[PDB]
Length: 517
Image (cartoon, rainbow, N blue to C red; front, side, top):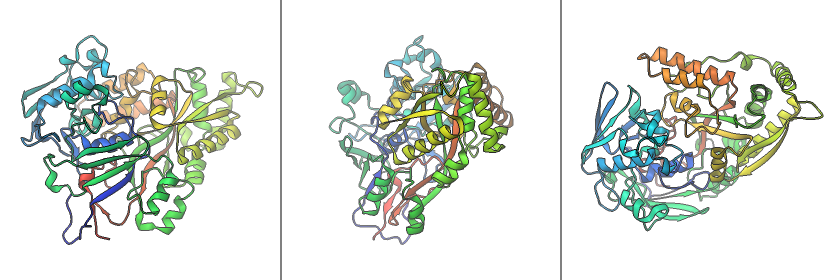
C-alpha cells in the first residue's frame, strides 16, 4: 500500500470482506470464479500483477522483454520467496504452467494457455504430447522464457490471472488434494492462509517472506462466503463487514444511496450479465428458440425497472467499453419491445410450440437475492411476452459451476468478467474447444474469425474481426445478453486504497489500509 501523507493509520490493521460465496478451491489450477480469484490474488503471485488502477505491473517478474511478440523473457526478482522462506524460481513457473496444461489436472482454465498461444498447447490438451513439451523453460533460476506459436502483442496482459500463478510442487506432490489446507499450504503472495472454515470464513495473515512485505499494511483479512446480498449489506451496516461483495440487493440498494452516499462505490466494470443457453441441448439447439428467448426478454424492464442500479442494457457478450471493442449494435436492440415480442412469438411458433404444447424449461441460478429476483422477473417476462414456462432452480456457487461445465442444464443465469482488458478475454470463451465454454457453443465460422485476429498485424483489422465475431455470436443467439455490470459495493470510510479505477476489479489486500476512526 502507498499511504498518503498525513493519514493517521488505525492501530489495528484488520479487514473483513464479503466474497459472495464459498470458494471452489484455493488451488490456482482448479478455480475459475470471481470469489476464488479474490482470495487467490492475496495468496499466489504470478509474473505480473495489477497495480491499484489495474495496470499490468511487476509481480514476481521485475522486468521483461519480447522478441517479435512471440518469445517473452521474464526476469524474476532475486528476493521473490515462498512463505516457507524458499525462493520462487523460474522452475516453479515451468512446473505450474505444465500442470495447468495437463489434461489430468482438468483445470477449467486449461485454455488460458491457448488464449496466450503458448507453443504446443493444443496437442497437450488433446493428449497428443506430454505437458513437458509446453513452450516454457527456465533459462536459469531467475529467468522464465515463454515461446508462443504466433505474435500476441497483448500477451503480458494475460499474466495477472490466477491460473498462471505458481503453485508449490513439493506440497502438491506430498499432500495431493489437501495441499491447500492451512497446515500444508505454501504461498508466495502478500498473505498466507491462517484458517479455512468452509461456509464460515477464510482468514489470511500477512506473509513476512513476501518480497514487498514492507509496503503491506493490513495484517489480517477475513473473506466471508455470504451469497445473500441483503445479508451482506446488513452485516456491513452492523459493523462486522468492511467491504461488501460487489453484487447488490434489490431490497436495499435505492435506500443505501440516499442513506450512506459516501460509502456506495459505483465504478466501471468489464463484466456482462446474460442468460447462458445450453446450445447442445434440444430444443435449445434450434436457433429460432434461442433467438426468441433473446428478443422476448425486456431489458428496459429488467435493467431500468426491476434492478435499476446503473447497469446498461446489453446487446453483446464483450462489453462495448472493453479496450479494443468497436461493436456494431444490432437492429433488434433498437426496435421497440413490442416488435421484439412479435418476432419472438413468430419464431417460437415456427419452432413447433403451441398453447397446448408450450415451451417449458429450467432456469438455473446460483443462490443470491439479486439472481433470484431477476430470474423471477425474467420468468414472468417470458411468460407474459412469449408464453413460455420456466422452472427456477437454485444451486450453490461451486455446484452451479460444475453443473454448467457438465452441461446438465437448460438455461442458466451467468456473468463473465474480463481476465485481461482485450476483447479476446471474452471471445475466446466461445471457441468450440474452450475449457470456459459452458454455453457448449461450437461454431466453425466464429472460431475462424477469432483465429484470424492474430493473422493480421493491425488493431483496426483486429477490432473489425472482433465486431464480426460478436455479430456471428448474435446471429446464432448463443446467449441472451441482459446488461453490462457496474461495480457497485459498499466500502467503509476508513478503508483506504480502493480507488475503483480498475475495471477488472483485481483488488489486492496488500494495497489497502485502515484509517483511524
